[PDB]
Amino acid sequence: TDSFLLRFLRARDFDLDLAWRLLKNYYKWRAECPEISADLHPRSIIGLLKAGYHGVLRSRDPTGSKVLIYRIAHWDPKVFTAYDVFRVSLITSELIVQEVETQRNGIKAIFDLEGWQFSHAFQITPSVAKKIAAVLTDSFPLKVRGIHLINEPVIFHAVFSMIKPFLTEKIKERIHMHGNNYKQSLLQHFPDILPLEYGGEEFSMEDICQEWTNFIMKSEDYLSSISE
Amino acid sequence: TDSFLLRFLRARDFDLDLAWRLLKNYYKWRAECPEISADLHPRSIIGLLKAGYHGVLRSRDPTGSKVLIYRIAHWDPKVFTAYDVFRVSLITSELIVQEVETQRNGIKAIFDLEGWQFSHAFQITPSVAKKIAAVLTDSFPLKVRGIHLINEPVIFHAVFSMIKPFLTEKIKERIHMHGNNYKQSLLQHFPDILPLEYGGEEFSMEDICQEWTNFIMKSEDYLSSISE
Amino acid sequence: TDSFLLRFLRARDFDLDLAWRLLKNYYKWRAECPEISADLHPRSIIGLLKAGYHGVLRSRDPTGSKVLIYRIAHWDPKVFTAYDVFRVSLITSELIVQEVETQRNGIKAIFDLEGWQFSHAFQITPSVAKKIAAVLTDSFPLKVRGIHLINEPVIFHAVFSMIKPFLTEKIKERIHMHGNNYKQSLLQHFPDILPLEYGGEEFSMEDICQEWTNFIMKSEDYLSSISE
Amino acid sequence: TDSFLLRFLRARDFDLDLAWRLLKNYYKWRAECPEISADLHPRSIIGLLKAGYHGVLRSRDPTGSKVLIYRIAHWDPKVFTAYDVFRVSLITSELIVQEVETQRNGIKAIFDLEGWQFSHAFQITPSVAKKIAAVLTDSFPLKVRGIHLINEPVIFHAVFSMIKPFLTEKIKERIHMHGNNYKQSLLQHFPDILPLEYGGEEFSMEDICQEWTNFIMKSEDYLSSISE
Ligand SMILES: Cc1c(C)c2c(c(C)c1O)CC[C@@](C)(CCC[C@H](C)CCC[C@H](C)CCCC(C)C)O2
Ligand SMILES: Cc1c(C)c2c(c(C)c1O)CC[C@@](C)(CCC[C@H](C)CCC[C@H](C)CCCC(C)C)O2
Ligand SMILES: Cc1c(C)c2c(c(C)c1O)CC[C@@](C)(CCC[C@H](C)CCC[C@H](C)CCCC(C)C)O2
Ligand SMILES: Cc1c(C)c2c(c(C)c1O)CC[C@@](C)(CCC[C@H](C)CCC[C@H](C)CCCC(C)C)O2
Ligand SMILES: [Cl-]
Ligand SMILES: [Cl-]
Ligand SMILES: [Cl-]
Ligand SMILES: [Cl-]
């Protein structure tokens, strides 16, 4: 069967030395952040999901990557903390990493930063920013093939300035900032598969969020299994 | 007669040490890429030529450089591979290098990247990208005086990011990206000589492609001679 | 045209550094042995040829190598010296090296040492032995793919002991000693192409010698051209 | 055919390392002095030739060297510059170097310095003097076997003092100064072949100059070929 080791091998192109280091950092990072990784049961973040914060596209991008969508406007920082929000991505990642094609072709994430407030950045402490850079680089068995930021306000760049120093040059090359006129540039990266709200043709974000919410709730037994 | 050595001397301004190194890399590169350079007979790429992928201007630029035109939209990656396409440039280069004035004044190439798809970049592997940088720098007796990219889509820069690390600073200075509004900037570099499709006045790309296709087919005996 | 340089490139697999060194040794060796290489006109060794000392097979071996045959019994050391005999091989080599397929696939030589006397070895001085090793290794643009010694007497090994210290390990691997029962082992290396005297089926050594003698005499104008 | 390389090999006794260095300096020197070597067409110096400045003996010296004669009195420094005069020697050298026997036996030059004025030395700048020493030593594929100065005035030694520091010891050994009573000493070096004006028996300098002038004008097509 697809062993737990196999996802780490594929993430590092069957370089046993590199895959081993990634495995070490995976356990290390999970140990230094139990407030995110100790309990992966969707119980603590179901409110976030039903608020419409997160969803995953059905179809893959032209290179076979899984496409993830985050909407920061649907995150209420008064209700959920940065750790809660982080846990959502962690939960999704632990699920999609089971897909062999995702293991081979990595993922791409889209962040709709419309509605980013000063109530969001306060949650993003230096410790949090470094943990963000960790999972983006060499602490989780997922190839980050691209990060796409749209509708990012001027005040956000201060937040990104906290993450960038801990980023490898490879990942920095893969982070895109589109601004408010994102639609044309975003459609080139993701043809046919985007939802209606982002220039897409068929499905809406509400449907996509609901579907992924169901899948997470459905996978609640597996998410408990990998909890320590 | 214009010896085979003479083209290497002129390419390095009669610096015998440098011209010798270029000769060494010329044979080395040809040995490490037989899937491109072993057989230069136009047989394997005649379909590409008649598709309208490549053509050479009759008139030289204001500095005497030969001007080459490539249209990526006329490359069907399902039919022809990157090696096939590479072979086209190799064939053209082996022909125009016979011109003494081309030896002295180098070449300039225009790439119409309109229609660049994710089906094109998949062909461009790290090994291919490094071979591209090789012939652009110090592995073929042709001075690359300028590379002009027009209509380049957003997704192309990821491909260029694979080539750039292997490029010398001199060549990087000579690579131009014009975007969609290229016509004004392109006409300044190439007055009077451009085809109709790119702001020109007289000839069309279809004529230019056909003429160069005829010349290549006509030179099929010479191209077989230099095959190993 | 097939330049004089090209034979040196092919001899060293288009390694310009190595091919250059071979060219240097080619001129050096020719300069330190004018009593062999100054005059390559068949005048001085026509008697050797008509005595039946040397011949070249029409057909190539299974790998495309030219096959050369020497019969030491037809060398009268009282009439011709070691330098005269050496000149024969030099003349043949300068002729067969013009064949592109010989340049690519190298040569193989068969020495019938039947009749090797103490009047032959006296001619083989330490200086001569070292010159033999020179052309076998890195002083002539011919790949020596194999040397086959048959009917070698016990007293010959003393002579070979003079050559061996100056031989590279590569060439030593390619020197074969078959003894008196050579026919079976020799036929495995050279199927279908051997003459009647050595297990062959069709042609005789006398015919083969005469044919190569004619060709050398016919090429007398070219052999004068390369004389210094 | 006698390749362009072959003249450099013979000039350095088939020492490939040394012949290669001479080739490098040949292109270097030609690049640092285009005001002498860019255009070798006899157009710019035909007046010098018809003035009777230069001629070449028909017969070779006892060692087979080509013998060149220069008469400084027939150089009008008001009309022709040092570069023009230098070009004459360059033109002659590029012609006589085609002779295989000249390649093997080198050249000898005779300078009649009778009439050397202070209007001649002003043309001989430090830069010019060093260029003179360059072609005399290791920058042109011609063995300088001897330089003979006759009728040299006292004021000339200041000019020679500018050249001597850049001369190798070998060439310095081969430079002879005869003075006004040169005839006896000059006849020992050049028996039977000298013109009437220098103790000769048959031909006059006017005939010799005219003959070489015709040959240069006749070779005007070749001299254009080697121009860059
Ligand atoms: C394995 C994996 C994880 C675990 C992951 C992400 C990706 C691509 C992964 O492959 C992306 C998002 C992230 C880092 C969660 C981020 C948590 C914070 C609270 C998000 C809100 C504010 C961010 C400042 C917005 C920008 C984020 C991008 C710069 C990644 O969690
Ligand atoms: C001697 C010589 C060769 C041999 C040559 C070129 C030039 C200017 C030369 O002087 C330019 C084109 C190239 C490198 C062939 C490229 C092959 C690939 C398949 C082209 C399609 C995709 C490219 C990623 C498009 C961008 C190319 C530019 C950045 C050069 O082949
Ligand atoms: C380029 C080239 C030359 C020039 C050449 C040979 C080969 C294979 C070449 O590729 C083989 C023969 C040789 C060395 C001539 C040998 C001269 C002596 C006189 C031969 C008689 C006695 C030899 C002791 C017999 C054994 C020779 C083998 C050990 C090669 O000349
Ligand atoms: C290949 C070659 C060249 C190119 C050459 C010469 C020789 C022997 C060559 O082999 C001799 C003459 C020279 C150097 C041209 C000299 C130019 C000047 C203007 C001559 C007039 C004044 C000289 C100060 C007179 C003395 C010259 C000797 C000391 C050589 O050009
Ligand atoms: Cl972008
Ligand atoms: Cl530009
Ligand atoms: Cl054997
Ligand atoms: Cl003297």
Image (tube, coloured by chain):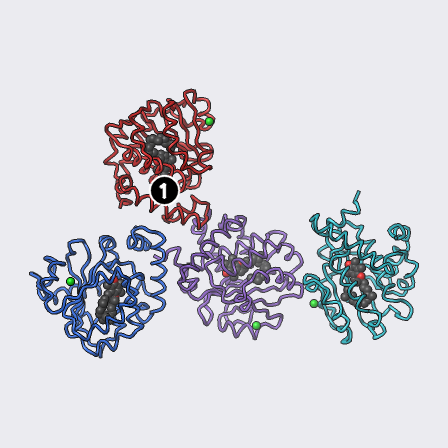
Chain colours: A cyan, B purple, C red, D blue
Q: Is residue D118 left or right of residue B188?
A: left
Camera-nearest residue between A178 and C71:
C71
For image coordinates 27% across by 37% down, the residue present is C218
The percent coordinates of residue A82 (x first, y second) are 85, 66
Helix or strand or loop: what does disc 1 sit on? loop
Residue under the image location 33 percent in, 27 percent down: C71
How many dots with numbers? Answer: 1
Circle 1 marks a residue in which chain?
C
- Other residues around mark 1 within 10 Å, as few (<14) / some (14–19) / many (≥20): few
Q: Does B82 sit left or right of D105 as displayed? A: right
Residue where numbered disc 1 is placed: C98
Return the residue found at the far top: C181
Q: Amino acid at mark 1?
A: Gln
Nearer to me, B199 or B83: B83
Q: Position of residue A165 (x, y in %)?
A: 72, 67
Q: Is residue A102 above or below residue A170?
A: above
Location of residue A95 in the rendering, given as x and y in whole percent from the top left corner: 83, 53
The quadrant where ligand 6 appears is bottom right
- Seen from the viewer's position, the closer of residues C21 and B15 is C21
Relative to B136, is C24 on the left or the right?
Answer: left
Q: Please, is residue A35 above or below residue C54 in the view?
A: below
- Asked whether residue C36 is in view, the answer is yes
Indicate the quadrant where residue D112 lies.
Answer: bottom left
Q: Is residue A200 above or below residue A15?
A: below
Q: Is residue A208 visible?
A: no
> Where residue D141 sits in the image (x, y, percent)?
29, 58
Using residue A29 as the reference point, say whether residue B158 is left or right of it: left
Residue A196, quarter of picture: bottom right
